[PDB]
Length: 264
Length: 263
Ligand SMILES: N#CCC(=O)NC1CCCCC1
Ligand SMILES: N#CCC(=O)NC1CCCCC1
Image: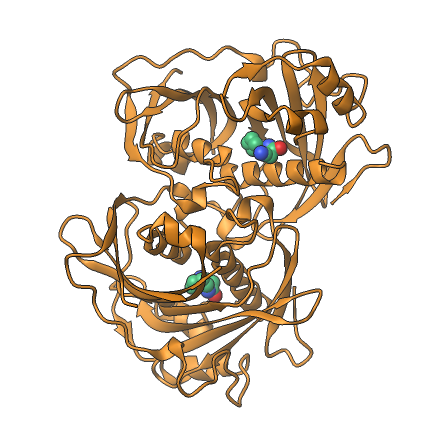
């Protein structure tokens, strides 16, 4: 991987692995999300980091608030996928990381993704606005004019998601993270939540449809000793679902989302 | 990746990923096991496949009976690891796949692994001996003289493993596979069982020790709708005896041992 000529974005190529593919012999959405995360981390390292100087002094971190992924073609086992990523400041609300996925052979766009990140104190877990000093320190690494993976004025990446009402149509109960689900700081990896959401989709939908769009809101973290319940209700040749992840016991919300599936 | 000059083994280089490392910023044993599995699959594809012509017509497949891994140094995040793999016939018993892990920069051996594979009919799930026809079709891709990742006489990779007796010292119950744990044929990936075994090791041990050796026997598969219990007892450096069994009737799925060195 490497930064582009202007130093304002980063590209990396990946060969899709045997254990990374599902029943169709194409990469799962969780493999795609892990690749986005890896290219995101390599971009941050290449430019000096994603805690800045001022963030480390004030015990502040970036946390994912929302993730939105749209896939047109999942790469097959052995195929090479090229991913381009960049960051942008969104004033004092937070930051945004965007991605474009391309087939290395054809150069065609096979997917795109966007994510919203908010500032948070590591210790108190209290969200806050982006200070001027932090915003100035990361603007040297971002394009100045807007560059959006989802430019459309009526796009599905900015839609408000409602809370699923009991009773859910489908459910998968008692989901727990194992050590492979944790990152290097022992926090549950953001991609695990995508897997947990998809666990309540019936196997018949997965067998006859391909996942086209997934929007996920992150409300609260799952601790490594927590237990989660995954709930899904059909809201709809296309199928839409409303999703909810909550703690198995008290029912505390951890995530909410929507998925759109197209018939194969 | 590519086959070596003589075409009797295969090498591939991997850059360790951010999500592939644990709390020590080095690759987990499950990342290592996934890399062994990937280089194994790439070796099979490069030589024409690991179902052969005779196996496809007879509805036969290779299944893992045992896996043994020894790690001296886990590669750090961003490091390049080079893995060499080869296969060997073991007469009528089955086949063996071996691996050597090296630091790409220094060329030093940082790990080694061996695995025993047995023939099985896909449909009946009945184990079988290897026929002469299969033996001949496999021998053109294997070294003729023995080449062993663990050559030492009376080494850890060939030790008989006993069955853990109740009550277990430690346990993790109600473990279930999710879709990310399944392979392309909807079977639970062999690496998931390694993760499930390690789930009953206390976090205190993981925080103060590094895993040096793991030997795992595969007795029966876990279906995607099955629930597993993971049991561990200290037998001792720290040694542990492990057992995975179905949550309900207690049917054995795996047994194994781990050796851990203090950091
Ligand atoms: N953390 C991290 C890497 C990153 O930049 N993005 C990740 C986190 C959100 C879901 C997958 C993509
Ligand atoms: N299947 C397959 C790939 C392969 O050759 N070996 C794998 C399976 C056993 C555990 C990890 C290594």
